[PDB]
Structures are given as structure tokens and as C-alpha cells.
Amino acid sequence: SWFEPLVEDMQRQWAGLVEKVQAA
Image (cartoon, rainbow, N blue to C red; front, side):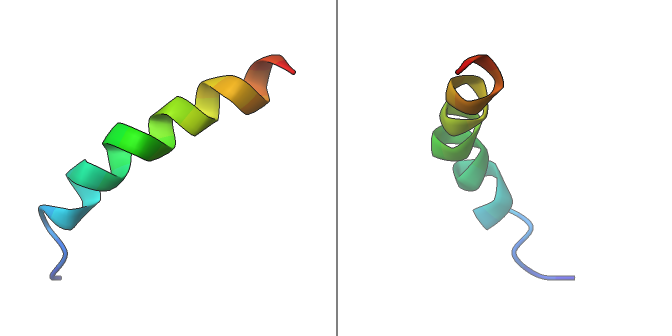
């Protein structure tokens, strides 16, 4: 329900993490 916009900021930093792990 909530955290509508908080998710998007989570995408900024956490998506950078997603690339690091995918590669190894």
C-alpha cells in the first residue's frame, strides 16, 4: 500500500548492487 515512492529510491542504490552480483 504505502512506500510508493520509497521503492524508487531503493531502486537507485540497490539496482547498482544487482549488476555487481550478476557478474561476479
